[PDB]
Amino acid sequence: MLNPIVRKFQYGQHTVTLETGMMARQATAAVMVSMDDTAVFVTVVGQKKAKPGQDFFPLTVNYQERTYAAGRIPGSFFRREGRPSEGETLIARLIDRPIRPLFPEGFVNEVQVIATVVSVNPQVNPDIVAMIGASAALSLSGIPFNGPIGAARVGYINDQYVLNPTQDELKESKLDLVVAGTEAAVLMVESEAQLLSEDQMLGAVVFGHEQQQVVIQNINELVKEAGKPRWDWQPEPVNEALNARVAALAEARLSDAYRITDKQERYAQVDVIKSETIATLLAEDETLDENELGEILHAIEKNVVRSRVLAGEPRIDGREKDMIRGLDVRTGVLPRTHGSALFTRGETQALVTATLGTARDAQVLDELMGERTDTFLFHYNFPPYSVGETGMVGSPKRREIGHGRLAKRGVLAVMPDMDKFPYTVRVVSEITESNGSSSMASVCGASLALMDAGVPIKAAVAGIAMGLVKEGDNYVVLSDILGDEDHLGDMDFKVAGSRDGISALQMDIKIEGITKEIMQVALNQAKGARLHILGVMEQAINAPRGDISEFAPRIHTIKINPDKIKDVIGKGGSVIRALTEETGTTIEIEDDGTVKIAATDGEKAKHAIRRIEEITAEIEVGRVYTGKVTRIVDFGAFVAIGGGKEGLVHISQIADKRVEKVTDYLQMGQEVPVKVLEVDRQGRIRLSI
Amino acid sequence: MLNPIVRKFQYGQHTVTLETGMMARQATAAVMVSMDDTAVFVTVVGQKKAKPGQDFFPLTVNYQERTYAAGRIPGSFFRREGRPSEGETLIARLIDRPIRPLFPEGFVNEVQVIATVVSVNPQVNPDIVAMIGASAALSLSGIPFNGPIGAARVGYINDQYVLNPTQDELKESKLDLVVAGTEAAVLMVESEAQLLSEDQMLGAVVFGHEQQQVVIQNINELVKEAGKPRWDWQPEPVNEALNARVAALAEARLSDAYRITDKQERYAQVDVIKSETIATLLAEDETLDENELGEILHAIEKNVVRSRVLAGEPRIDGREKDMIRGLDVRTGVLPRTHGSALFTRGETQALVTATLGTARDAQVLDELMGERTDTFLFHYNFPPYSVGETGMVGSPKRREIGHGRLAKRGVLAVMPDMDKFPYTVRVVSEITESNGSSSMASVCGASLALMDAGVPIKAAVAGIAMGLVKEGDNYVVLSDILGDEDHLGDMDFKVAGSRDGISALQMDIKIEGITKEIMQVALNQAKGARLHILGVMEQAINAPRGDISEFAPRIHTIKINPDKIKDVIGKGGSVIRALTEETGTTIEIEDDGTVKIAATDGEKAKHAIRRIEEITAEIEVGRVYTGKVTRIVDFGAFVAIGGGKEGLVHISQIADKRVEKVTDYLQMGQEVPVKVLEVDRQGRIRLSIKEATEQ
């Protein structure tokens, strides 16, 4: 028989179970993690040998939300689970971000971790469960890994931190901050936040890091009980028996070259010293093969810039450590789009557009927790010419979707709630050119494009991409980092939010010994640079324009009395069908208390108002008035006062006298006095000659 | 700061704007182009050095219609733009065809030009805006390129030409010709026409070329103001001693080999002397192989055939200049299909099929220009076995769409109007074998398959793929060119139309000096070959068949009153769903009471008529049942005229107050028949003792 090893927790008043040892025995390791009636099966396979022509490390992650886990049949025509959506692909990225730095330097063997959701109760989100499982599975396997990461989701409600909140706490919460870290340090931070201050969110991360300690302790128990024999993988030695000679021949001139002011002359001189030292040392294989020699020269370049940045003022572009690049910000740039903007920051440029739509058009996405409507849609397009090089159109990847979601979190915090503004809005960003941190340039552009469209957005929103360099006790916090300056980042972090408070924070710490002391001054420097940007944006547009641009659809609403419903509906929706086809306009959106008119243009809304007021309780008459002869017989006449239908006036009303014959009223089209003058009564007219 | 550079020529009665230097500054060039307000952002990136040992030119073009440009959010479930589409990959082909020949010979650096539509006004089509933008972007970049190209769309209304017509001007027009050219020559022409004559179509191309020199002038002043420096490209020399030496060792016998009458012996002898010279001739610029020597032999082969064709009548097929391949035609080839044909023309063959459908099966086409729902659908399938090769069936090439649209333009003109013929018709063509033009063979087959399915088309249509070879004052028009006469096609052109006139025209010119005198004699030779083909097509079948084939859906209508309409529906069309599935018959509700009915045969439709009348008729009439029924009670009785269900009746209206007792019979199971009396309180049911439709 087979037997399973089982451990239990109490993690934020939930009972986590790490079952292992009875499933997928051919895989390098496997665990089923369940937290509360919610379970993910996660399994690692890592081959022992990689083809010696492999330079990069192929860690790969897949996360799959099998719909049977929610106990219901798929909605797709093929009745089968489809491609990864936003939802699967973003969760695959959050699991990958903490695991990739923990693997040892120069580890290159191919590793694949596959996480399947197999149960859910709607109250508990599976992503945090999958993160615990991935660190358990990797640390149970023999594979070289620097200790198991925990994970915590932290909510903020009634000025109190709440560990691993349910959907019921999160709908009320002002914060959704996720932490992942080892025993020693935070490794990843991610959040949406309702304009909290810096010291509130740096409280949230350290609370989240303290609470996840139980998970890291329990995984260390399970690894003692059921852990495989460890791998003996060792790296190739650092020197490769040429390090010192090439360092001596390159470094003197190469370290000089970065003093040169002109980007072109600097690049040229660096290429000259590189090509000369490549041409000089052609004595052997792996010099006649440039690759190993060139990889060493590229490493010298990184070392010389890194040392300059710590002590000396000049950067890769000669700016001061904190000197943000120049801005200019055009608005209303595109002729027929609802609102549009062209935000720039050095050589990163983000053309952004906002587009407005009716209650019909909104996205109804289906996910394991629930099928649900939302009304703010953000799409991020990154075409290849943006980086000055050619390839396949679109070029879609996890990073481009990551950047889309991060930007949406930044400005979703500051969107109006539906009662102030009833439209669905799509914001769509074309990255016309990029050389670093294009995601934070896209949130600045979205803030412009919404104000320019005349959405009642609460406040202007901006973002900055920072970094930090550290050596022992020495560190420098730098602002507006380039793509070329990525090597200097021991802590890549992005902050976006209004003057009042921050909308989003994201951090990829790559190294041990970052502290609550350091993160305080780093956020305090980001506050400065972010308030500088808003100083320019407030001059380019000052407040959202009162009136929505002329090409947008219009939605508006009027209050109605409880008796008017039968008049608005008619018989089997006949008056609705007539009104909608007269007006080319949908009106069904409300029918109790109010009616809502959702029109393709302003004239069609006015046309709808005219027609509904000519029908809805317009038939009733209380005083003496005129309305024409419309259709006639001997027995009486049909007489029109308005748009709403009017029945036969009997000839005994029409004629006072005995005769009652059609000769008295034979003339068609005649204008005549007509007052119903009748309450608590069926439809009648007291016209009398 | 950034500073955009603008210019604003007047062209087509609209205001145009060439705005540059503000966006995508990392890209080799970029332009925002805007006419009226239908703006496209178009940018080119071309790498400075070509990857080693390349042979073909990897120019790539793609064009993307972002939906936000029309001011609406996407209707897709993902609420975002996905893959390219029929209406965009075709437009990319229209941008590519005039650009591709205009690059210098031996240029093989990778170039990518990408056009995004960013605003649209529904009256002005963005495609012509993209063509002037692509010309501007390439000529502003340092890329070696033989000057700018303009593009013009020409309409015909009241016997007068109109430049750049609106959608309003176009819907009334008998023509939709697009022409693109430099100041020298009309590099591309592409056109649907409502049976215009030769003089009218060749007038349209010269008009459209005269009044677009303004675009090429304004691009030239912008290139002086804002153009980057022309970067240096030099052609790889190909003029070694071994070129002349291999020619000397090949041309004489290659001339001797091309004299051979038999196709098979010709191919055999050419392959032999190729194989011999590949095996023998040393001093190749690499260890001895095909990799230049075969490409040099291929140049001799091209020169020999081309010179023979200019000097004298003989070709590779053994036919003369004005000659057409052998034809065979047969019709009704596929059973259980509404109509089918097998048009054949030497080694080119198309199994064309027509199928009819309802107004409901019509495909809605969504564009930036608004919805463009249509009723004649053309699909073009080119499987790999058609050319005697293998692999990757069913994944379409850009030219499977390209050829499909050209064929649709050819047969769109002769389709009947909706009131004379109400069915939506899909024409599908399988190219069963091809070594010649497959698109013009598909038009010939489509006109057969529509007549065979009995669609009341105006006239039979055919098409021809001409070619022209030119050498100084020498030129020859070839009336029907194969798949390996490609090197002889300096002017590649395809024309399809009725006896009366042209329905579609397409020309790719890739030589200078094409005068109107040349284009007249070329079209006049196409007229000859096209009338020959109709001579065979008319002899296989004369006119559309008396009515549609017995399997085809026959649609008809009966008028019934609105109280029966609600009774045919029930709730949520549930009675329609039941009756339509029971009868296998389609129906449509209309508010005037004329319900439409469609089935594959008469009897199924008649069954549906009978059932909806019988079910929605009042209960007063019906079958003459013996009303023996149980469940009789003193305080009202349940009585069924028919069926298991038992309806109610009461002490008074059982027997029109003739008695005080509930039933005069006063007996359960008694035989007296029952039918409804009209009176019906909503909370009451009436089923009186009534025989023989007493009512």
Image (spheres, coloured by chain):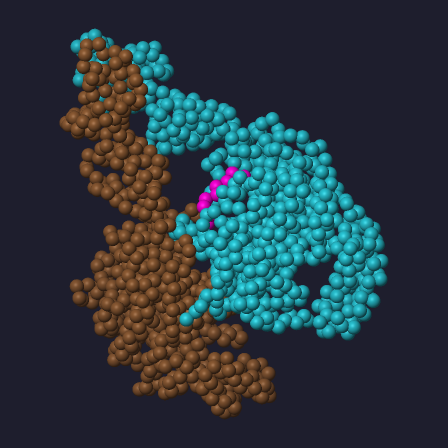
Chain colours: A brown, B cyan
Q: Residue A41's spot in the image, x, y percent? A: 35, 62
Tell me: residue A654, above or below residue A128. above
**Residue A604 painted magenta:** no
Residue drawn at point x = 37 percent, y = 71 percent: A327
Q: Is residue B479 left or right of residue B413?
A: right
Is A550 above or below relative to A64?
above
Instruction: Name the spot of residue B109 as percent of width and height, x first.
Output: 60, 68
Question: Who is closer to the viewer here, B678 or A501?
Answer: A501
Q: Position of residue A638 (x, y in %)?
A: 27, 21
Residue at x 53%, y 53% (from the top left corner): B11
Q: Is residue B141 left or right of residue A156?
A: right
Farthest-out residue, left = A680
Q: Residue at coordinates 56% horizontally, 86% vertically from top-left?
A: A276
The number of numbered discs placed on residues in the rendered structure image is 0
- Which quarter of the rendered picture does the C terminus of chain B lie within? top left
Which range is magenta? Answer: B367-376
